Every structure is written in structure tokens, then in C-alpha cells.
Length: 18
DNA sequence: ACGCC
Ligand SMILES: [Zn+2]
Image 1: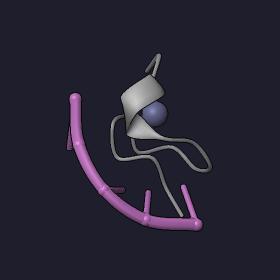
Image 2: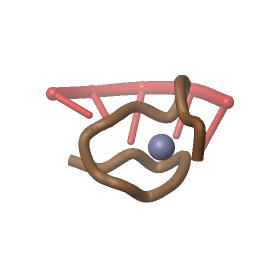
Image 3: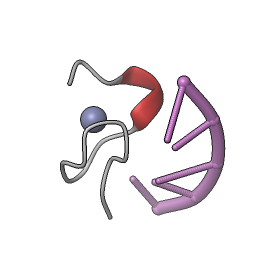
Image 4: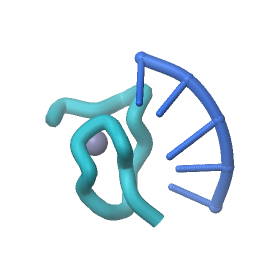
């Protein structure tokens, strides 16, 4: 499933570079 | 940023 911070796949919002 | 995986 996807990150929602960026909308990319296979990592977690809390930690997002974006 | 939050939640889930
Ligand atoms: Zn992300």
C-alpha cells in the first residue's frame, strides 16, 4: 500500500522526505 | 500530518 504523505508506494507518511 | 501495509 501507499504512502499518503507523498502518494508514493511502500513507505510511511511520518517519515516522508517527499 | 494521520492511519494501514
Ligand atoms: Zn512519502
